[PDB]
Image (cartoon, rainbow, N blue to C red):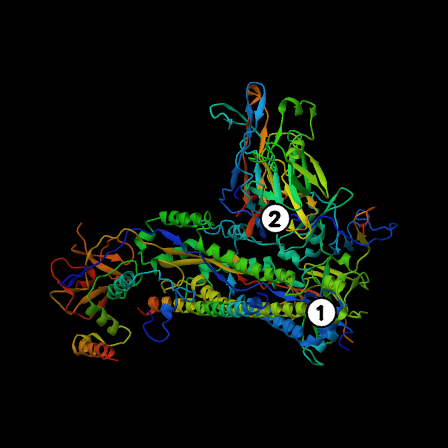
Amino acid sequence: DQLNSSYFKLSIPTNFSFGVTQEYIQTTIQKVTVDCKQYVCNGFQKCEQLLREYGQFCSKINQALHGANLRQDDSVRNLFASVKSSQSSPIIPGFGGDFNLTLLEPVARSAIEDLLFDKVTIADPGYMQGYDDCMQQGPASARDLICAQYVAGYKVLPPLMDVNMEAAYTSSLLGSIAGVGWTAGLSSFAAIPFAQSIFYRLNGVGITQQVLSENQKLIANKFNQALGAMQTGFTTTNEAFQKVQDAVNNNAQALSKLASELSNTFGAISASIGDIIQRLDPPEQDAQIDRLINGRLTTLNAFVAQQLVRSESAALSAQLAKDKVNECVKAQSKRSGFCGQGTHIVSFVVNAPNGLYFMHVGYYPSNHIEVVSAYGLCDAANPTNCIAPVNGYFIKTNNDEWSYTGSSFYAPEPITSLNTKYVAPQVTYQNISTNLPPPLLG
Amino acid sequence: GPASARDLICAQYVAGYKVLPPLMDVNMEAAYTSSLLGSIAGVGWTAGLSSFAAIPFAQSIFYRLNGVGITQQVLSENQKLIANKFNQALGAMQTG
Amino acid sequence: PPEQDAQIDRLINGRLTTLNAFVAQQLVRSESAALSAQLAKDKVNECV
Amino acid sequence: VSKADGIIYPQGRTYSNITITYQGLFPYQGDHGDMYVYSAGHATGTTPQKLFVANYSQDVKQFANGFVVRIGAAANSTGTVIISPSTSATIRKIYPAFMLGSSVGNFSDGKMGRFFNHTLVLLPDGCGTLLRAFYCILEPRSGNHCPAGNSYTSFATYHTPATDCSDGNYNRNASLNSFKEYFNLRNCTFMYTYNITEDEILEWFGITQTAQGVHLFSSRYVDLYGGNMFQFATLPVYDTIKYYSIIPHSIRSIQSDRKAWAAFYVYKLQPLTFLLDFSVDGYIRRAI
Amino acid sequence: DCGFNDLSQLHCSYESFDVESGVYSVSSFEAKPSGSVVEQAEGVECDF
Amino acid sequence: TDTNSVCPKLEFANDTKIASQLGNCVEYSLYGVSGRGVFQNCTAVGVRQQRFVYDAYQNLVGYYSDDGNYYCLRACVSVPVSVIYDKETKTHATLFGSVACEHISSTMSQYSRSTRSMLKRRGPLQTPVGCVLGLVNSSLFVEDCKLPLGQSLCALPDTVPGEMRLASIAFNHPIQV
């Protein structure tokens, strides 16, 4: 409620309660090429020599897919030139002193990134010898899309990067969080411990003055509780994990439509060219093969158009991911809602299938007592000497009449020259005379 | 029946399409924007949105003017035509 | 019936294609509105 | 259909661990069908002297797309003897008999239910150990209680457990002699026979008509402990079956040897789309 | 000659004699049948 | 309609048995159904009396043979081909999809392509992305070579130039403090 006097009411909290927001940004789609001639005319000489009248449709399809894949490679190359950190501190098994970090690498990926890739249903693409595994075993189960290649006439291309170079990039990013996120310009790199960085981030935005941050090591306990409670729930209730699964499913559906449109007849006597050749004579053999040719060309054009739309959107979300790495991971953010909820403290990022996975640790206050508070304090004898608080409030303590509290946690303190600034007088300022804070003494 | 020419909202139940209701009332949307209006002065005064200083709207406007629109204290305490100009702007809004 | 079917098939195909076009345009429209909703969220946090 | 009741298996193929939509001839979910029951005859103290049937002969039905039959569902349990409602005995499986044809009318005294031209007849025989299928002209015989005679109520088949069902020696033409008492079989094209193993388990039967003939499906010989029906015979009947009726059957037993026969249910088939669930071993245990 | 070579079909699409560093996928090799298998009914003939 | 078929009469002195050509690409005419594929001995999985086992996409994946075995079909395979081209040097190389180097030969004579010839050199080299022809293995590292092969591999041209060489993209470590 809003008072009528020259005071106001405060509603200040009494809990830290670190929380994790856990967002996912997609940066790429999987690269697919289509062998147009093989897809349409499945090795049948007659069909190919009927197709020669459709020469440029296949060229257009091939060129469009080639351009889309080049764009995907450019997007990943330019995203990982900002993820790159100029200077970094080596990762060692005990990295955050009292803060647990399961973001370290088990001798490669990290534990949370391994878990993210395991919990997700991804078909193995087989870049090494996926050719051999498909008759030494064949289709693994129903609708083996990653093995329907080498049959249908499409191919899944490998990503530009290993898992090892991607892990190297995100590890060098984790090794700079404390040091680049302390000072101004990212020209220099102060190699300070992680605990010092957390205490400076708390003393700063999540305004909690030095007395508390040096009066608690339950801060590390609450941080560890938040990070631990993260790594249990990669379940269906987790909404960013569902987005990762959605992206994987979109890749799979894109492939499955190609695989499934080869059994369509488009009105012919059969969907097999060999059957048509066997059953009919050339005059109407041609008329039946033409139906399949046109049907398959139109489905393939539709595939290309949808692939262009998908790559266009993924190229924009890659820029969003670059903005989040620069804004949330390499610095502490003043913007609300951009990184997570609460007030942003620190963010981490790992690789996810087809993109990046962010964990935003923020500060969540719980128990709000009210308080009565003053805009400023002036000396009654000398009403020109007036002070105001910095990053905090003047509170009427009920336990000197006036004390100081930090902005984000209720813990009253004596008023000193270190938490006040001299200001011009104002009608709403209190004219105290009896017991006078040191900054106001003459 | 059809209110006038091309009654699209009534061509449903005929054509075979249907317009679904929104997720929210008008009352819950109004509640959201009213709770947003009721925090403008208080969250927009200090740092981190962890605490909420319940100050009047005039104090918030004077701190916003003394700050960005850098106008020192002597003026902001020397004018109440500031409120007149603010009211002129808001009023001239609701005609056009 | 022999050509009754052939005439009804024309309507069936025409209506299915118009309905597919409607669905595709609706997907484009919803995709753009979902981005402008993020812009509105940014403006509420930044400006209000 | 959650138990896959009355499913004809797809004709030329099989699947494994898959869910498929299939267009086929299926019965309706929750359909009740028509229930038929067979009873013992009048036994006046160790001498059976009069049959005891229901009114099935007059009740000519439509053979639209074929039908499926559930046989022996109530077996292995206790029920009543139809002729004497007070008496109760263990229920036993019996097999249906059918007359199918393309033209139907009435007998001499105006009773409905006479098939005119070549007629398809399916009769069990051998105390339920063979199935006999033939296709020919039934000319009604004269004499007392015969369709061309006088005092004609309805035709029926019968078999005598005392003589025709002796262990080890089952009369394999009993209940075909019975049919020959009311009718004379003239000018016919086949007389096929299929041996049936004797047991007391639930069984499914089915019949359809295509340009290839008359197809007979059963649960036995492929899926005995499930219920899936696979084709086992194609009969050379090319005139379109349009009417069918159930042949009444009564046993000539004795008050000591009077027992209860399970009722069988007939359900019609329509062209429907179904969602079928093929198990790993390829059987349908679930449908929608 | 468009069908001579992989680079040839590289050039015939792009319609040019100086194709850029266009790193195609090109047409694939398909296996040749090393044999033939036949099963059918034995010892029975359709009776006309 | 049936699990059997009505076929013409053939000459009964041939070697057209599944059990002999087990594992290699063959034409098949098992019954009314025909195609190309690779057969394997395999554990029986469908309903035996319905001799053909299909998948959700309506194509054969299994067969109950007259010899008493169950064979599961495998769809004769295609080798993906890709050309690595450098326009300034006019040099080229061949990347064979994701295949093992022992499925390919200098002439590729057991396959058909409808491209009459194949790029000319003057052996195969196995890489995490597949088998390459016309690249020489090197222990070099780069920051880029404009010809990424995938999996952090890259094809370095020269500057009569020799064969392009297979380098790997290197991670440039930051200053370690």
Tag 2: Cα neighbours inside 10 Å, few (<14), some, or many (≥20)? some
**Badge 2 sits on which subunit?**
D
Residue A268, which numbered label? none
The front one of F128 and B9 is: B9
Mark 1 or 2, closer to the camera: 2
- Locate residue B33: give its quadrant: bottom left
- Where is residue D237 shown, x and y percent of the image? 68, 48
The front one of A58 and D194 is: D194
- Locate residue D217: give its quadrant: top right
Q: Looking at numbered disc 2 in the image, what kind of residue is underneath it? A: Ser
Q: Is residue A107 visible?
A: no
Tag 1: Cα neighbours inside 10 Å, few (<14), some, or many (≥20)? many
In the image: residue D218, left or right of residue A435: right
In the image: residue A423, left or right of residue C35: left
In the image: residue A68, left or right of residue A98: right
The front one of F54 and A430 is: F54
Q: Is residue F113 above or below residue F65?
A: below
Q: Which residue is mark 1?
A: F83
Q: Is residue F27 visible?
A: yes
Q: Which residue is mark 2?
A: D103
- Locate residue D150: give its quadrant: top right
The front one of F3 and D157 is: D157
- Where is residue A226 shown, x and y percent of the image? 41, 50
Marks 1/2: CA distance? 74 Å
- Where is residue D82 shown, x and y percent of the image? 51, 28
**Badge 1 sits on which subunit?**
F
